[PDB]
Image 1 (cartoon, chains in turn blue, green, red):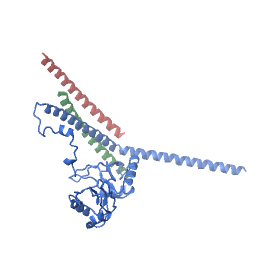
Image 2 (cartoon, chains in turn brown, purple, green; image 1 turned 90 degrees about the vertical axis):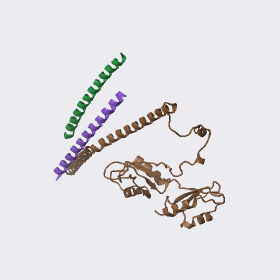
Image 3 (cartoon, rainbow over the protein chains, first blue to last red; image 1 turned 45 degrees about the vertical axis):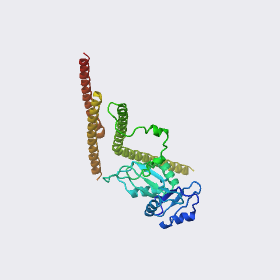
Image 4 (cartoon, helix red, strand yellow; image 1 turned 135 degrees about the vertical axis):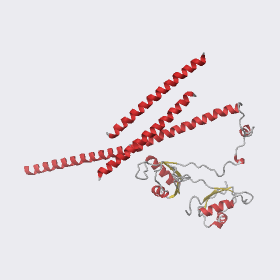
Length: 273
Length: 41
Length: 41
């Protein structure tokens, strides 16, 4: 969209004498700007751009450019209003998430995660605009049961972790302490069979494979429980219909009896006088 | 090792058998629902 | 009633298969014990 959190940009390593006027002039090549949140002392703040195209152009055109003897470090700000929604219904659309979670606020975009074949993965990714809407939606969908469609399966909603695969691990950002040297005595390589390394790596591989077996066992248990729970839907639905009908009929018959007795008593006391 | 191989073979057989039972049961449920909706009309 | 009778039939089939697999496991255990006795001597 326009004026969203994807157009937002984090600017860092600015000179301490930056100005809001020169800040706007700095991005003046890319149309208007949003919230000019800047810190003179620590040298970084929050800036907002207009659209996705302009943000993609400007951040990559502005990084690696020194400014007053300081090579700029501008980065994509990790989105804060993020949610993730799970156990989505078998039939779901982008606009279904855009409209359902529109109740809790403005959904800038929610897009059912899809794999290569086109089938849904079974998860979701919802990015509101503001944080408080995200908190309210998360707590409500935790305490409530946010049904999405006729199929009565509520969607579990969790906060999303920001796995950053852009900056990776630059060399100069590692601690490089005595442990690093202790861990960099010998280069990466294979383990010679029969050595200490090979045996201890066999121990690690056994541990990892047993962990994977445990995870698949949990997956199988949940899958069989879910398949059992989907089949007993009809029986539970019909039983609840029968219970509701029986309670309603009890209520109606008691209402009839009370109306009859009140009419009888009032006519009796009327004719007595 | 021998016990582990035997156990995994038994587990695979059990999974296949349970899948067959499950598909039979869901087929019965589908036919049953079809009978119900036929009786409704 | 239909669902319960189907479930009972499924359970009977599962029980017979489980007993067959238990018999197989006991036979394997006996054969292994024979092999261990042979190797010990």
